[PDB]
Image (cartoon, grey):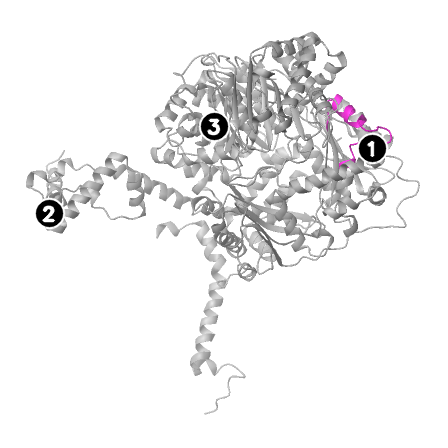
Amino acid sequence: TATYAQALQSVPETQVSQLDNGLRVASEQSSQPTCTVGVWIDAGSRYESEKNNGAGYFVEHLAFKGTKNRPGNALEKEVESMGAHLNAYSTREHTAYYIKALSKDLPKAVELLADIVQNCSLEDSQIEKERDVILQELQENDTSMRDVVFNYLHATAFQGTPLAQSVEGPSENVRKLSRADLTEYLSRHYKAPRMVLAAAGGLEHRQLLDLAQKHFSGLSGTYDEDAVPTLSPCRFTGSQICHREDGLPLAHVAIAVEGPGWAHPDNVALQVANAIIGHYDCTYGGGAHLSSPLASIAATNKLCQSFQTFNICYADTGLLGAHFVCDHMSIDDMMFVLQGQWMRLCTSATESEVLRGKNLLRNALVSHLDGTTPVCEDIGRSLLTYGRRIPLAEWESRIAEVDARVVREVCSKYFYDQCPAVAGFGPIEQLPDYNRIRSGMFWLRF
Amino acid sequence: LTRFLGPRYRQLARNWVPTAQLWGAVGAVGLVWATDSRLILDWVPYINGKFK
Amino acid sequence: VSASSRWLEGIRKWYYNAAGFNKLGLMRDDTIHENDDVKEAIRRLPENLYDDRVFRIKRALDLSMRQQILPKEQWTKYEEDKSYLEPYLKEVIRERKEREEWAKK
Amino acid sequence: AGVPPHPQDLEFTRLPNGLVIASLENYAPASRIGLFIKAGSRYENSNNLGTSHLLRLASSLTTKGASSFKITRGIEAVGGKLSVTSTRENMAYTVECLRDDVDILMEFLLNVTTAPEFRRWEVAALQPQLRIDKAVALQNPQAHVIENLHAAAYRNALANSLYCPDYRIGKVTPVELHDYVQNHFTSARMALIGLGVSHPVLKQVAEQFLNIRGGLGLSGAKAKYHGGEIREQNGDSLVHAALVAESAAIGSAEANAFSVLQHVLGAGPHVKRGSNATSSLYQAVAKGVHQPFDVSAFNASYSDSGLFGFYTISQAASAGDVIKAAYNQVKTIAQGNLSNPDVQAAKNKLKAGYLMSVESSEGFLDEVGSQALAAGSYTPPSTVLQQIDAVADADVINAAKKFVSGRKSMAASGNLGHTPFIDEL
Amino acid sequence: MLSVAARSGPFAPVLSATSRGVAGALRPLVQAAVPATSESPVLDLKRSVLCRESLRG
C-alpha cells in the first residue's frame, strides 16, 4: 500500500563528508539521469560594511565572465556545449553558484565550479562593463514595487545594522568599487570552512568527494588566524517607512515583527499559523469559499489584488508577517482584517484549522523538494544554517507536534503586543498611522 | 442554536474561559470597591480600617 | 389518497382562502419574509420568474394602497399556486447547513 | 549505504474504449493525478469562442457529488491543489496531495470533469474572472504576439484564441459549457495519469467513472495553414516580433529535426547573465546591433501542424535590422553553412534539456499525459534520446530550407515604424 | 518528446484553486533583462509572480 509516513523513510540519507581544508561535501543520491551541483558560500550583504555594500553582487556579475584558466567566452561555451545551465544568486546571508547538468557531466561541472570559486579573473575592462549593467539593474529594480517594499522593510526594521543593507548596494558603491575592493572581499569570505559543495541526482557520494579533493584542495597550507569574522546580532526596531507616491496605481505594504531565526524550533509553529492565514491572489479560483478568513473576506469584499505571509530567516533574527497590494481606498480594511487574524490566532486558535496549516506545510515541504535543483539547494543552505540536513521524517515529526495550544503560545511570543516594522509604498494616504497599527497588535478583549 | 454545537466551539469556549473568568474578577472587585460593599471588604487586611 | 387526507387538503384550501393573498393576485412565495436565504433565492431566480414576481408584488401593493381586491375569477387558485421559490430556497438552506457543519469541526 | 530503492517502471494501459491509463509508483511522500483531455482551444468554433477558457476557470464550481464550497474546503483541509492547465490542443486537470489523501482528491477530480453542474448563477458570477484572467496574462507582450501569431497562421482551429475574446466575456452560456464537456470530455479523448498511485486503482477508477462515450471523433477539423501577418501599434518602448513558417506535426521524424534546428539557432539562455556564445541567432544580430535586444528560435508543434521560426525583442528603430539579421542567419543554414560539432552542441542542449524537463513530478506527469494524448503510448527518455540522435545534419539543413521557402506568418507589437512587413523580408 | 513545455514554444495557461495564474512556454525575455533596460510592466490591477507553495521547513 505504501503510506505517507512510510514514504518519508524511503528518501535516501544525505551523505555529509568534510575535506581537510574545511570544505563540506554533501550529496543526496537519486535515480535521475541529470543532477545539480553547486557551491554555497556563507556570504551576503550582512557580511559587508557600508563602504563595500555592492561587493557580493559585483562578484556575482563577474563570476561567469572569465577565469585565469578559462578567459572570457570560455566558461560560457563549455557549459553551453554540454547542455548545462549555469546559475547564481546572492541573498543578505548566502551566495550560491550551481550547475544543472547530465550526471555523466558531473566531473566537468565540479571542475568548472572550482574555477569560478577560486580563480575568478576580475578583468579591469569587465568590472568597468559590469558597473553600467548593475546601474541599469538598479533602475530596473525601482519599477518593481514588491522588491522596493521588502528592501525598505529591511532598511527600517534593521535600522543602522548590517541587515538594513540591500544585496545590490547603493548607486555610490557600484560606481566607486575598485578591483582591489572585490579581491579583498573574496579573500576574506570565499574560504573553505564557509563553503558547501552540494549535489543532487544520479551520482555516488564517493564520486563527489574524489572531485572535491581533485579541484577544491588548495585552500589550506595556512588559513584564517589573523582575521576571524563572526556575525554580530542585528537590532530590530519597531518603525515605519512611508514612501508616498500617488502616481502609482496600487499601494504596497509589508508589515513584520521580529522573528527568531534559522535555528529556533518554533519556526515550524509560526509557519503553520502563516499557512492558516496563507496567501491570496485575484486569479485564485476559490473566492468566497476559501478556508483562510483573510483570503475569503479579501476576495468577497475585493479588498486587495494579493497578499502573502512570510517568515524570512536570518542568523538569530528575522522578519515575520505579511505583504499586500491593494487599491488606495482598501489599505485600512486590509490592515484591520490581517491584524485581527494574527490576534485571533494569538488568543483563540482552533484544532481543525491548525491541522489544515500542518497539512499545507507537509504539502509545501514535499512539493518544494521536487527534482535535483530544489534538493541541491536544500543541501547547501541547510548545511550553512542548521549544520546538518534535517530529514523529511524529522520535519514531519516537528510538524505533527504542533496543536492549537502550540500555535497560540508561539504566535503570542512573537506577534502579541509587539512593535511591527512597517514598509509602505505607493498611494498610501489611507495607510494607518503607526500608533493605530501598534494598537492592532493587542486586543482589549483578551 | 444547533449550529453552535461542535468540537471547534468547545475549543473556542475553552480558549476564552480564563479571560471571561478574569473579567468577572474585574467586575466584582470593581463593584465591591465602587459601592464600599462592607460584607466583602471586612475580610481584606489594609482596607479593614472603618472601626464603628 | 385517503378520505381524511382529502380533508387535510380541504382544510388547507380553506386556510389558503382565508389568508387571502390570492385576492390580491399573489402567489404563496410572493408573500414570504425576506431573510438572507430568501434574498439569495430571489437573486437565483431566472429572468422570467423574477419579472413576473416583481409584477405580482407591484399589482398587490397597488391594490393594497387603493384598498381594493381583484375580481373573483382573477384570484390565485390553490390548485395552481406554483411554488416557484421552493427548489431555490431549499438549495440555499442546503448550502448554508453544509457551511455550518463545516464550521463545527 | 546511502543508495535509493530500485526505480519502478511506468505501467501503461489502453482500454478498449480508447481511454489511456498510465501510472508510476515512485514511492514519493506526495501524489499527483492528471486527467488529460483532447479539449483545448482548437475545438471551439466561431459561435462559441472562449468556452474552453471559462471552463478552465470553472473547476471549483458545484458538481453533483460536491458543492463549490466542499471542493474548496475539502482540498484545502488536506493541503491539496486542483489546477487546470489548457494549451491549444489539451486540457489537463491536475490534482495534488499527500499519498494518504488520493481517494478524496480523486473523487473531487472525477466530479469536476465528469459531473459539473454549471449552475446559471454560479457561471454568471464567474464571467468577470475572464477579464481579470486575460488582463493578467496579456501583460506579457509575448502572450498577445503568440496569440496574434496563431490567428495569422491558421484560418481554422489553432487560430483560436486561448483566452476568451472580449466580446464573448459575459456571453458564454451554461449550455455551451455543458455542450463542450459532453462532446470533448469523452473516453477516446481522455487519459488518466497517476503518480504515487498503484495501476489497479487507476485502472479501477477509469473503468468505473471514466467510461464516457457520445462525443467527437478524430483530432478535430484538420488545422489548415494559411499564413499572413497581424500588426499591433502599441507604444510599448520595445518591439516584440515573431517570424514563423509551417514546420512539422509532433511525433514525426521531421519534428525532431526542427527541435535540433531550434537549438542550433538558439532557444533560452544557459548562463545567468551571458553573451550566449553558442547562440547562432544572438551572435548574428549582435554583430550588427549594439543596443538592448533579444532573439530566440521559436518552435511550436501540434497534432496536425507546426510553427517554426524566431522571436525578437528590440528597440523600435532597431526592429528591421534584428529581424533581417535573424532571418539571414537561418538562410545560411538553409544554404548548407552548418558544421557537425554545431549540431552536436544543439543535440546535447536538446537531450539534456528534455531530461531536465521531466526531472520533477510536475514535469514528468505533464509529459506522460501529453504523450498519451498525442501518441497513445509512452516513450522512455532513452529512446527519445535515440530519436534525437537519429537526426542527421542534412535533416537540420532541410528543416531550415523548409522555413526559408515556406509562406510566412508574422505578429508584431510596439512602435512598428521600422518593423518590416513580410513583403520586405 | 510530445509536450508544449518539452518542445518549449507555444503558450500554456494555468488556473488553480489555491495557486497563482500562470502564462506560457518559450520565446525570449530571460536574455533581454541581461541587456538591462526592461522595466517590467507595473502592478496595474495585477496578480503576483513566483507563485507560493515552495516554503521551507
Respond whether the residues carrying marks 2 and 3 are from the same subunit.
no
- Circle 1 sits in a helix, a strand or a loop, which is it? helix
Local packing at callout 3 (Cα closer than 10 Å; few below 14, some 14-19, many 20+) is many
Residue D332's quadrant in the figure?
top right
Point out residue A144 in the picture as x, y percentages from the top left corner: 61, 42
- Circle 3 sits in a helix, a strand or a loop, which is it? loop
Q: Visible in this render: residue C84?
A: no
Q: Is residue E2 left or right of residue A236?
A: left
Residue D104: say if magenta.
no
Q: Residue D295 versus residue A337: which sits nearer the camera?
A: D295
Residue type marked 3: Tyr
Q: Residue at x 80, y 35 (%)?
A: A126
Residue A198's quadrant in the figure?
top right
Q: Residue E52 versus residue A65: which sits nearer the camera?
A: A65
Q: Is residue C105 above or below residue A17?
A: below
Chain at tag 1: A
Residue highlighted by disc 1: A114
Q: Residue D38 versus residue D151: which sits nearer the camera?
A: D151
Q: Quadrant of the N terminus of chain A?
A: top right
* Magenta range: A61-85
Residue type marked 1: Ala
Respond whether the residues carrying marks 2 and 1 are from the same subunit.
no
Q: Residue at x 69, y 25 (%)?
A: A32
Residue highlighted by disc 3: D163
Residue A84: say if magenta.
yes
Tell me if label 1 and label 3 are in contact, CB under 8 Å: no
Extreme residue toward the left, this view: C72
Residue highlighted by disc 2: C18
Chain at tag 2: C
